[PDB]
Amino acid sequence: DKTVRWCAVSEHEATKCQSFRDHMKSVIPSDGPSVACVKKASYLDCIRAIAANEADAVTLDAGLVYDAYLAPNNLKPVVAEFYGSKEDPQTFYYAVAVVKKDSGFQMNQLRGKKSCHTGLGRSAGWNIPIGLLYCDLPEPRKPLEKAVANFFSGSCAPCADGTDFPQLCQLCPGCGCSTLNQYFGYSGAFKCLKDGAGDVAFVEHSTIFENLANKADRDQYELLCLDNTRKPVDEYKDCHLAQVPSHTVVARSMGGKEDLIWELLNQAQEHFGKDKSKEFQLFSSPHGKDLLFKDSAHGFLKVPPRMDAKMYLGYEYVTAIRNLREGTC
Ligand SMILES: [Fe+3]
Ligand SMILES: [K+]
Image (cartoon, rainbow, N blue to C red; front, side, top):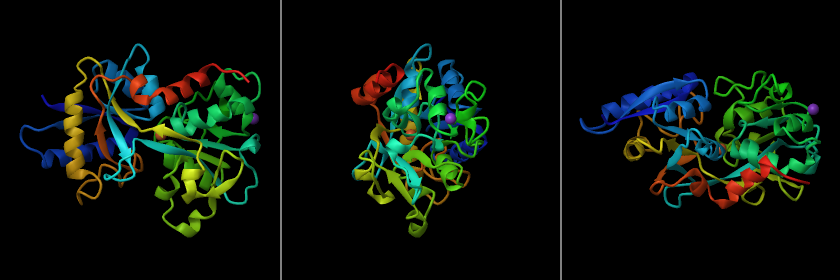
């Protein structure tokens, strides 16, 4: 069998997955790669399913790539997203802090504000913004969750526990770990800001561009820079929190079907990648944004053989994570 079982988180990803299954099925040889769809409530359930041989592949934020390499799962990174263009591909992106024009505050004046995150554990939504703001947080700083809940005056951290940390779900009651939470992910953290529930969205550089097509509406938003100034959203290259490694597909170490994962995704990149097909798209969707793969991706690059999360992610970002887990001020 040449079937990749894809893990899709909730109703909408599940739909795009069935399209993906059907179009590949229709425009593929008798012998080529098939994909099957397994619906899960969260990225955590996908990670558990892949370790337990009940699924083969899920695409995860760089932060969640790290998380998934830890025991007893030991998921290995297999295919990387790239952004920008197919000519000069990039395997990183920019963590930006998006705010509404004329809101007043800057970064060392973020205390007491409302925060929209993509989700707990994610690079630009959590790890980067919270690590930089770590010593600004009140004591005690463990647990970290409870202490960012204390810093802001209400938050939305998708995937967090709302019993243990009610405040982290104030802007999105429940802290849903899927698109079913309307304020989950990139597009969801920007909807959280736009609706006026929050003051800052910790998102990627291309987030606003994919959620607001009109430049006149776009100019009512700006970014928070590290020198405590503000700059137009277009000038993200000189006003960003950090550069983070790209979302990756992960797979099992043993019997991971990584070769096939590549074969499927690479063929799928030629048939349905950016601007390639009017029947199906891999990096946009009728059913939502950033489903299965991010909207801002332009295709895929193969991860070198048998490389682990640790190595793929790089020392600067692995180190950035570990420092967050145990620090001092
Ligand atoms: Fe991300
Ligand atoms: K508070």
